[PDB]
Amino acid sequence: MEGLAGYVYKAASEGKVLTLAALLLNRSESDIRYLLGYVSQQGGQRSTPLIIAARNGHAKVVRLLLEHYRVQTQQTGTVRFDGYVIDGATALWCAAGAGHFEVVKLLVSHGANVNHTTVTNSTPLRAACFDGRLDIVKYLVENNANISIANKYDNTCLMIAAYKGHTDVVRYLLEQRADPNAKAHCGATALHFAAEAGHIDIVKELIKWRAAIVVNGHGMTPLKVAAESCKADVVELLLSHADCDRRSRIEALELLGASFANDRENYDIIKTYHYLYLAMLERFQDGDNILEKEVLPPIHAYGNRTECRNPQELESIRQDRDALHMEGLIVRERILGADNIDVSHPIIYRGAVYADNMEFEQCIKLWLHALHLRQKGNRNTHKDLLRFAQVFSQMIHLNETVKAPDIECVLRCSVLEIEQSMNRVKNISDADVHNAMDNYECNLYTFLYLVCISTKTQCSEEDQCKINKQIYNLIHLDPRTREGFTLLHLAVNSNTPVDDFHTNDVCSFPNALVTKLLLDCGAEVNAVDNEGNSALHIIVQYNRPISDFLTLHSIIISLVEAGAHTDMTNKQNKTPLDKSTTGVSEILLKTQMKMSLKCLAARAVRANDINYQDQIPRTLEEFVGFH
Amino acid sequence: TCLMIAAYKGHTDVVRYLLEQRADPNAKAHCGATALHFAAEAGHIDIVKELIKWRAAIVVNGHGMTPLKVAAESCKADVVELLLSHADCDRRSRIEALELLGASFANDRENYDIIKTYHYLYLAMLERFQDGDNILEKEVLPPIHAYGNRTECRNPQ
Ligand SMILES: [Zn+2]
């Protein structure tokens, strides 16, 4: 029966009245009304024949359905655009999103319900604003569309239209007395959206309506937002339209200069120097009436970090573009503060370019500041910690790493914290965070790479003690992976994701020193994965015995010590001696294997099937289970 | 022939193309060395694997020098791995090759790894006494004053 629904869907997508009529003809009234009510979620989005006709922009099909079949226009579907899914949208919403003017004309002329209840509170006017068609917006608004209707984020149609940057729709909505004073969830105003868009005409139109200057939650006044977005024209327009004190305009000018210097997109130091010099002359313009200048305390990350306050002080800094950039960073960090996370992007970039070729030191300290900032926030830094891993690989390849253990201890604390946080995240839900489970695995890999870095380097015994404190903190809590794998199991298996930036002379699996240090920490040797495979069961399977024979010999002689059972059957009977395939690995085991009567008795009593339940001390039940 | 000299050089693409022409790789020279010997000297594991793929058999030169032994002499472990894996051989030849590899690591200047030599010889000799009550014999040549004591070891102690 659903085949008829698919045929109607295809006919609606085609746009032919003849095919759709023929498919709907020779069917009962109930059948055709069920076809109209049915939604074929081919892409997982509800789309009734009217809804999908509106989305596909076929005027003929929409006209036929509305005129001859009386399909309900109040049907709402969770249509998705560019991956993002709106959880509710009527037929008129899809018509506006399609961008076809005849379809929206017909649907509105057939009494389409513009105001439809929706969990996302989406409206067809918002869809038209997203599409940007002025004519569709006009036709929707004229025929009973409430512009004041906003989504769950309190984002109105006018707000998103100003964000888009289309001057026509903003002008039309302002003509229809659309209120721009509504506040979104963040509380930003329409002036903030216009400054972000960078359209001077939108800002001028908003000023014409006399929109109030309202500071957002994290500061971010419209002049400050425009200065951050490098909208010099918008900043000048706001300063001219709204009177500001000396402090406000001087701060705006210096923020604009520092933003121009710091960002890689602009990358103009002459404009930055000119703006800073102008602002500081404005500080001293009056004469004996000087704006109070504060100096941030010196920080080892920024070096001297002396914020200059006199004209000769910047005059001495005409050259040394690095000094100008770091001073702009100081200015931006002082003005903006650490309240928001917007300053996360520049600092790393300022490190990144600095990280092109040099000792990495103040780059590392800048990234440490970025780490602190991102750890105040609940923002995932697994990509960032990867980047630190490749940077460490770079410096160890350069052989000039001379690494300081304080930084590695700090990043170990951070990675432990994020491990715990994302473990709780998986404790909340699983399906949505499957990619977060992939990041779980990746972060375990990063810790192994950090352990490989620590093994390659060497430092003071107290620093090693702190490293071992952190690794024991990670070990005491028992990490697990899909199908179950301890740290040792990864450390002995062929860990597929070897660092691509540096895969040679660094991070090679089947390592001996890593396993030695992990045993020193005290990981549970007799831990069993799914199917019960022990550590020895995933080291005798090595396929290159004659090469790298030193590694195999060392790992075997290390794991045989620290108490590892010589025989530990698991699921189907597989002794470590049976599973070995090389033909060379058996020798190393049989040299180190130590015999005892317990093992022989257990093998004898399990080979034959004798009852061993409730006739044996409870401890030996597990012993018999092993052998 | 271009085949053996290309194998000596180690250019994988040209050797692969020449083999594609179905040229017989069992050709010989005045020295009697087959392309396997030149590949072993080059040590390209992929070249040797490709040669084995199309049925290149081990052939002994008149003065001994089986390609496996020749590869073992020049301290080329990977070729030894590959040939031992594919080319079936007895206990005696395998242990002889392992001992030769140990000695070559011991004395030569290119690698000069004392521990690798010790461990390889230890493994070979442990393989010698594996069975028990059926022991491969070890023949010791009379001492040479050039080496001083010049007496080999046949007991693990
Ligand atoms: Zn036992």
Image (cartoon, coloured by chain):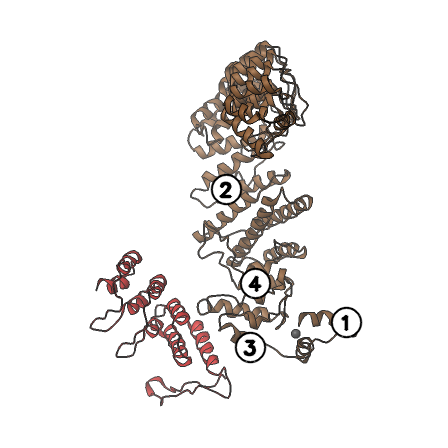
Chain colours: A brown, B red
Q: Which of marks 4 and 3 is in front?
A: 3
Judged from this view, the residue extending furthest toward the left is B30
Q: Which of marks 3 and 1 is in front?
A: 1
Residue that carries the numbered disc 4 in the rendered image: A515
Residue pictured at 61% horizontal, 65% vertical: A534
Residue that carries the numbered disc 1 in the rendered image: A613
Instruction: Tell me the quarter of the image containing the N terminus of chain A.
Output: top right
Give the label on residue A590, or none. Answer: 3
In the displayed structure, A289 sits above or below A346; it is: above
Q: Nearer the viewer, mark 2 or mark 1?
A: 1
Q: Give the residue type at disc 3.
A: Lys
Q: Give how far apart the Cα atoms at labels 3 and 1 are.
A: 32 Å
Check whether the beta carbons of the residues at disc 4 and disc 2 lie within 8 A of each other.
no
- Identify the secondary structure beneath mark 1: loop
Give the label on residue B60, or none. Answer: none
Residue that carries the numbered disc 2 in the rendered image: A363
Q: Which chain is home to disc 2? A: A
Residue B119 visible in the snapshot: yes
Residues marked 4 and 1, same chain: yes
In which quadrant of the rendered view does residue A451 lie? Answer: bottom right
Q: Give the residue type at disc 2.
A: Cys
Q: Give the residue type at disc 4.
A: Thr
Q: Give how far apart the Cα atoms at labels 2 and 1 are.
A: 65 Å
Q: Position of residue B122 (x, y in %)?
A: 46, 78
Q: Is residue A273 left or right of residue A427?
A: left
Q: Which of marks 4 and 1 is in front?
A: 1
Q: Give how far apart the Cα atoms at labels 2 and 3 are.
A: 53 Å
In the displayed structure, A43 sits above or below A460; it is: above
Q: Give the residue type at disc 1.
A: Gln
